[PDB]
Amino acid sequence: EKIVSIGGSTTVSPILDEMILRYDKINNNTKVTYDAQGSSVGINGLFNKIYKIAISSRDLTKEEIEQGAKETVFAYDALIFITSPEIKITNITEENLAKILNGEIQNWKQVGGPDAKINFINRDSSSGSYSSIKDLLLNKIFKTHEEAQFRQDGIVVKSNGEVIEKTSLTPHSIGYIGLGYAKNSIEKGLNILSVNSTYPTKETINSNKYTIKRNLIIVTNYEDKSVTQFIDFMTSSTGQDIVEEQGFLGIKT
Image (cartoon, rainbow, N blue to C red):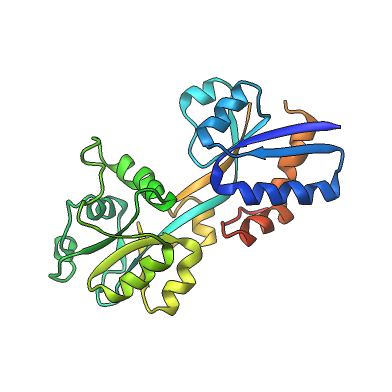
């Protein structure tokens, strides 16, 4: 029997677990396991021969590449920005969006919108969504730690569904939710913004034209056949159906 020990991001545990059990229907001669203590721990475990594959929700560093790391994307965790429907703005650049998030822009007029104070609805700081927006927008747009902090008087809520409800009740408001909640936001009569003139769709997220997403990547360090086989399953149509059945966005196959 072959053994493929995998480690990495906590966010994809039930996807990896289902992939393991479904791949076992095809090939019961490999034992695959997933231990989810985080992306960085997974990559460290890969380099130390504890894992043969790491699953990461963050981009590899140059040091990791220099140590031989290679990656293939297999899923996306995208976020979208929703507003109350009386703000007529339909599009925002990443730069301006980051300045709303960090409090440098606090009235819609500052970007040509109506004269109306912005009510920013933020997520709780323990959430994955908060972490993703901080990492994807604030930490990339702003040079210093002090600048790369959220506006401190945001209206804080503890779930995607509550961002939608709060946005529906709060005038001139903006919040962020996972892509999977787009339908719910529309049914509630809210508006989803384009970012850099790009709406978040499977095509624009796959092309990397829509910028607000984490790329979930398979990381290896010539692989064992057992590893190649499992990765081939992960990126297969069945693998990708599992990704989407569990609320993430798949790649093209």
